[PDB]
Length: 572
Ligand SMILES: C[C@H]1CCCN(C(=O)c2cscn2)CC1
Ligand SMILES: [Zn+2]
Ligand SMILES: [Zn+2]
Ligand SMILES: [Zn+2]
Image (tube, rainbow, N blue to C red; front, side, top):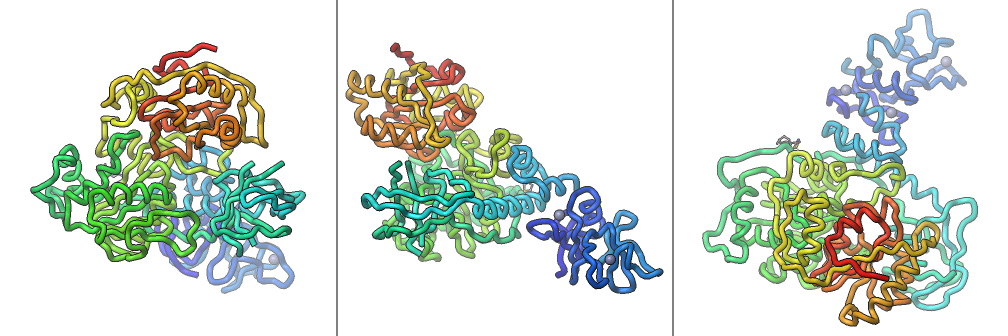
């Protein structure tokens, strides 16, 4: 009932009752909030409501104090002070940006821009309000009842009438009834159970709606610069493999936190694991939002770090199969690999937060709350894909607004930059270097002469809103017959429905651009499918073409991105 103001920290008994997160607001800030917004309900020990029997006056601007009680203009006694006077709301211990965060629906890009350009306390308020709004929105979709079970991976579904149907992709995870977590892909629908269960008819699936806990810690702790490496002890015997990062490792020990921008295949995992070899006594917690990113760090650690000092932290409510080679849930091992939502309450000499473009400010703050560290290292690339913003429908979210770390990397620049791409053929490196890296990314490999582009719009059909381009898949099939080395290629597109069609017609393994992030393949076949803002996003385009080690075939819809591809053009 009593606490600190989310705008100026001033102690108060006031909480805004119309805010979904009921933030503590001081007399001055509470007034400036209620007078400028539709939010008029204020809560101290008791709510600011008219104490007269049967009276429904809840608006703090229409209320007064009659001794110790509160009454409206129609019930107040002769000796009564208006609650809203002289720029203040009466209570105990006697903002334009806060108003917009407190009242927005989170469907505009300007909402996310503000949630990142505001003060540190408003970034936490915005991140809590957003996540709570995203969860209360999950209650809007319809329930799925099972109609017929055809196979162990296919079924028919009956949807709730009157309530919209959720997009059927891997992003939407349903909880079935407790029969385990389940996912769906497109009359026949493909089912994937986290737990293997004999799918019963009539059984129902509902999207998992979880409680949003409040944020305490900042997204970024206050920066500290040191004259010497602090609390870390370097080797003198450091392997030549990691010699290239020694200056950067020293920078890591001379700052409270550091940012590393690593374009595709420039050495992010190598840098992250090498930091352990450079400070061999240091306890390092390796974290990321996804299980795939945490597993990719375990893969690199398995190669260089001692297996007995590693532990993979796996939450008991296991949703996907993850890294099985380290001792599980041994929180006290020198090297702890764990997703952000599973982090324990612990300390560390270094915390490495990988795939930073995927993190939200909610995740940035959670890490600072669970982990007390001497040093924090943020590794990622603001030119890669951010976390999906399910509520955002109007406007495009620029990289400087993905989270606080990404904002710093795009404004003041990253502290460290891995400038040499060792994965991609030079055609790909030169294309993305000009596109998203200001011509600062360099190619280690030569031009492979196996990078092709085809300008082919085809025909766009739609599975609900997920797009399909059968003529683009037909062009791929003709190319495959003439280029049999490409049999081993991974098929990539911005749409899961395009991928489902390509899987049946081509038989190639499939991946969306968003699920391909962090992975690499010898050959990639990419069909743009449409000319939407989604398929034309330069960050998605960057991730798509940088998956290839040897060759890439790009069947393009957009003239702009097609012309920017420094690939050999093909006819038909
Ligand atoms: C270079 C100098 C100024 C700009 C970046 N900065 C922050 O924005 C920040 C970190 S934690 C809170 N604020 C602090 C460090
Ligand atoms: Zn205040
Ligand atoms: Zn409010
Ligand atoms: Zn009244």
